[PDB]
Length: 130
Ligand SMILES: CCOC(=O)[C@@H](F)[C@@H](O)c1cccnc1
Ligand SMILES: CCOC(=O)[C@@H](F)[C@@H](O)c1cccnc1
Image (cartoon, rainbow, N blue to C red):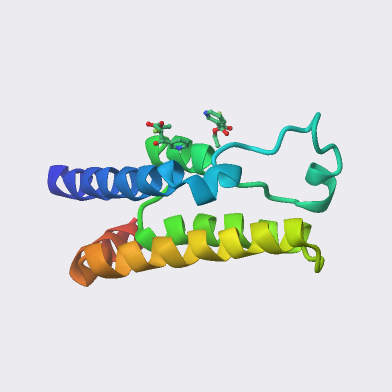
């Protein structure tokens, strides 16, 4: 229905706003674009599903996300990719792990404060009807 298409349009507006707020935070710069294969040729052989905030904006606009749960699976993948590629005790690895955990926690805290639980349940029930 038109009303269901208006529901998904409101979901996309919400997700673009959360993603922009993460992308302007200086702590999260390393997560804003894909890894450059020139600078890091090893990356795409270790990490099997790369993800970054520019790719997330592209996916929102391609209508890939019909629920906040499916958006949060991609935020979780940005975080888990950084934890697995950078697992060592040295300061450069510990700094990116702390930033990855902060990106994940910040996204979940904005959604807890600003997403209505009944709006998410509506999106889940339209998705499940298709
Ligand atoms: C693509 C939208 O571009 C902007 O407006 C930026 F300010 C910011 O939103 C941003 C940067 C990088 C990745 N995703 C979002
Ligand atoms: C996931 C679908 O989108 C793509 O594959 C790329 F275009 C995307 O990663 C990208 C990078 C930098 C600037 N704008 C978009």
